[PDB]
Image (cartoon, each protein chain N blue to C red):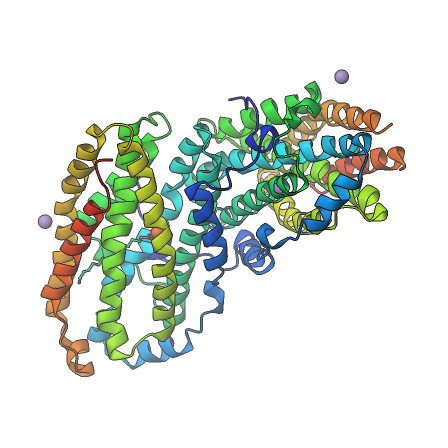
Amino acid sequence: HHDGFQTVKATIDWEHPMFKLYEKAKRNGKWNPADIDFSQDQKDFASLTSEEKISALPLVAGFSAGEEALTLDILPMAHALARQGRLEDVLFLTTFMHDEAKHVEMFSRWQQAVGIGQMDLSVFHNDHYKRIFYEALPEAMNRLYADDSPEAVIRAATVYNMIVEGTLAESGYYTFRQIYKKAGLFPGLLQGIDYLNMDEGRHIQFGIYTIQRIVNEDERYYELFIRYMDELWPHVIGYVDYLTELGKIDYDLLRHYVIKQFNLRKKQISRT
Amino acid sequence: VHHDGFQTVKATIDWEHPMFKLYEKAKRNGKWNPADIDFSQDQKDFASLTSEEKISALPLVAGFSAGEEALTLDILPMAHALARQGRLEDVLFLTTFMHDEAKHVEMFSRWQQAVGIGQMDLSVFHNDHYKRIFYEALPEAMNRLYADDSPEAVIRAATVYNMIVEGTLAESGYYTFRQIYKKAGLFPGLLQGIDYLNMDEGRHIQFGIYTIQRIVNEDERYYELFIRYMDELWPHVIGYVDYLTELGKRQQQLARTYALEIDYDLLRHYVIKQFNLRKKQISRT
Ligand SMILES: CCCCCCCCCCCCCCCC(=O)O
Ligand SMILES: CCCCCCCCCCCCCCCC(=O)O
Ligand SMILES: [Fe+3]
Ligand SMILES: [Fe+3]
Ligand SMILES: [Mn+2]
Ligand SMILES: [Mn+2]
Ligand SMILES: [Mn+3]
Ligand SMILES: [Mn+3]
């Protein structure tokens, strides 16, 4: 049952950080994947040899599954914060969920346009990738339906926002730019990446806000965060190594960048 | 719970799915931002009103504000249950649905803040019938879906949420706002909001129609479940409407001041009409 309603007893908390982030999401989130012109991507793709075509698909396969998992798996976070009465968080999360839906749409439109919609790209998900996206991520978010304790929320935000978004996604945007932007290939896709990268800045800020406000309550939670981060690193790097190994471009630069993101996300949370 | 795979890796979005097409319309038609609405004239209007006229408008606003908030929170179980069923295109659309309702919450709250009543507790205008619908039956029907996503459960959730709350009460609220405040020329920023809300609502009701019908299409038995759940909530729909009416009939000074003949019998009949029209938008097959 509802005991009452915040915007009937009072108003929105206009100064709340997540209301501010919601306002910025509406302002900066107007893009529409249906407006991206993929015609040249299609031509670029067909101009590749079979072997070059294949080299492109692992990274797209990681992203398409990623965007789909994140669209589905943010719902428990929204439910748990809703149940906690965190109205402004929920408003923001409506823009978060809608962003990920557009991200799903973007990669699928690209697949459709370049002619691989009918191909099953699951073959490029190795065991490490499945451990994160098929298993650890949904386990950690679905937990929130029955256990919204500080520890559960931090673990959910660590896997979703600091690992998948803050570490793999950010590294994937950089990777696309280092490989295809220099080659002049897939300009529609890279336009998409630009929009996704901009959305991701807000998504990561929500993860930081969430984790830090729980840490501020008890610095014992800081240790949990670092522990959950380190528990996932071997699959992050197991996946990265798998991708790198297929690519054989400075692949060792890209691998540094993953490490640099991982440590950056740890340093964005304050012990105190 | 594991993911077994992902549609957009094995295949693509179903580009021709009705809910993907509704999703596309939502993105095209749903750009409006409540932060862009100018309420400065509304603030002047409200302050020019006497105390009796000031409170004349508030029962309706109280009903909407809680409605918007309830609907923002309570659509999340429907999105979960369709996501668990693998209905990706429905989920895409529901992201636009939930964002619309968030903007609806924001719109009414901005208006309350702007006119100077954000600090007033408007729960006093929720009678017993309203609470039966919005504080109880609605969250019960939606929350059920976390442990019972059966056709019977999904039909009941869509009925309460899309056909009763949206299709009957919200639609009749939009109409009432226009018959009264648009006629009198008051609260232009609010009415701009109401028109955006009304446009959004069309999609929300169409999702409800799609959902109920696709279930009825699998077994006609469910059509009579739909009708019975509609009739079960009617006494609360009309009990709330009568409450608003009785309030409206005893606070006549706004109508007098602004030269309006508020036909409350006409408004009642619009609500009855909406209830029966929503019933008729569902067929046995
Ligand atoms: C080859 C160098 C390794 C670079 C790392 C690339 C990882 C690919 C990204 C796949 C997961 C993307 C998750 C989506 C996040 C979101 O939608 O917010
Ligand atoms: C005086 C005549 C009464 C007419 C009926 C008035 C009904 C008031 C509406 C309040 C409930 C609105 C629910 C919001 C629904 C939504 O956000 O989709
Ligand atoms: Fe994201
Ligand atoms: Fe609605
Ligand atoms: Mn390994
Ligand atoms: Mn009664
Ligand atoms: Mn994304
Ligand atoms: Mn609404």
